[PDB]
Image: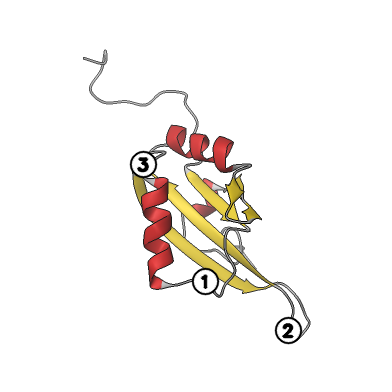
């Protein structure tokens, strides 16, 4: 028993969504990648879902293209681990950077922006 069946504590809502960057160019992105990243994350903990978002961040016609890989886990703890580790992992001839995303905004499907801005 947990000294109670229903109720809530003064605990906060940690972020369980890790965002990988500098993983792989937008060219390697294939139907296989997703799976590869999924099985690779399985190590840390139970992978809830993965979201791949990419876009242009330069006015130039052929500017650079970044890649934002979101990895949602079952719990915050697990996510923290993958981050504390992948936060400086070594990729096959490249460097990996795992940052912590914002759950608050993650509540909705607003990637480009954060939260539904009044206007």
Frontmost of labels 3 and 2 is 2
Q: Residue furthest right?
A: 60
Frontmost of labels 1 and 3 is 1
Q: Tell me the quadrant of the picture where the C terminus can be found.
A: bottom right
Q: Secondary structure at mark 1?
A: loop
Contact (Cβ within 8 Å) of mark 3 with mark 2? no
Residue occupied by mark 3 = 74
Q: Is residue 107 above or below residue 8?
A: below
**Few, some or many residues within 10 Å of mark 2 (<14, 14–19, 20+):** few
For the residues labelled 2 and 1, the Cα–Cα distance comes to: 18 Å
The residue positioned 50% from the left and 56% from the top of the image is: 70
**Residue 14 seen from this side:** no
Residue occupied by mark 1 = 28
For the residues labelled 1 and 3, the Cα–Cα distance comes to: 27 Å
**Few, some or many residues within 10 Å of mark 3 (<14, 14–19, 20+):** some
- In the rendering, at what x and y percent does residue 19 appear? 55, 52
Q: Is residue 70 above or below residue 25?
A: above
The residue positioned 26% from the left and 26% from the top of the image is: 6
The residue positioned 56% from the left and 43% from the top of the image is: 86
């Amino acid at each position: 028993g947990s000294s109670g069946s229903s109720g809530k504590l003064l605990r906060k809502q940690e972020s369980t969504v890790m965002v990988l960057r500098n993983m792989v160019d937008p060219k390697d992105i294939d139907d296989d990648l997703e799976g590869e990243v999924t099985e690779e994350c399985g190590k840390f903990g139970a992978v809830n879902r993965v979201i791949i978002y990419q876009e242009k961040q330069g006015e130039e016609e052929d500017a650079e293209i970044i890649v934002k890989i979101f990895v949602e886990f079952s719990i915050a703890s697990e996510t923290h681990k993958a981050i504390q580790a992948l936060n400086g992992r070594w990729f096959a001839g490249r460097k990996v950077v795992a940052e912590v995303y914002d759950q608050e905004r993650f509540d909705n499907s607003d990637l480009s922006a954060s939260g539904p801005s009044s206007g």
